[PDB]
Length: 162
Length: 162
Image (tube, rainbow over all chains, first blue to last red; front, side, top):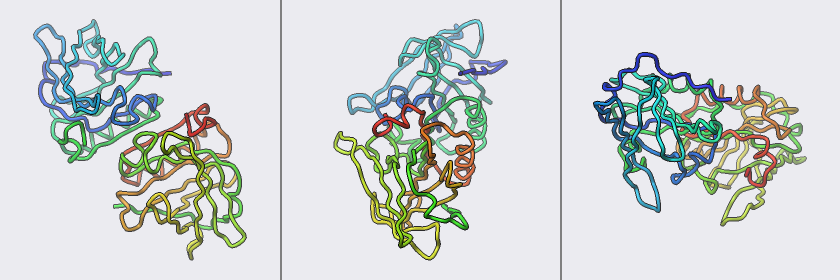
């Protein structure tokens, strides 16, 4: 059973800018297993809009190419929950952030959480932040994850994390 | 830097019989990333020999087929360390076992540990043993792992963990 805890007091305008996907984890192995896995996506930029919506710019391998992708997330009554329709997911969920160093978020499809949940640890610089990873693992300890990936600085600034 | 701690007082004859790979983790993502990854291997049987050597029977995907494989491990002066020449690894390292429920082991290539280290949690029954996984994660906390997989009962009794 998946229960996510979203951030209290999120100010979405402060997440703006460049990020790097330091780590990711998912409920089903197939979601992240192999570079072509559906939720193997690497966040490059978060771009809040004046409406309080959010554009997510990411990279993703598809048909052998490292491709760009833009996901549009719509605000909801809860500030840390946004609605999307992409990657067969329907929610982007912000778990925690300090704006300046790390941000934790998940995606899921609320109709099928155990088949769809993937969460990431994002960082502002392409370095490994052990404190951020500690917060990430803390959150993940409470979730039924079956796959976990953690990247190094070389992979962080690679194209599609190679 | 990899430092492994091998089991004190291992009696190899007691590990005999059927096992299942409940979980696995590795230092480099590529070692386990995708079903075809080099160290994506699923242990079926451990067969100690009268000499104190060890045959390891496993399954592994290769060229689209779920294939059988036998690895012959030679004893060394340390009872929990065996020598092999397979999967580009040269050591099998037993970390801990209670013989009756779980067994923890790694493989590595001592010439290049950070490029080669993969460890597993094995169990006697195709069920999930949270206590065994706790011991596994405990060991892994001290190691620089960058990928982690945990399987369910259906996968445990699948062919090549599908």
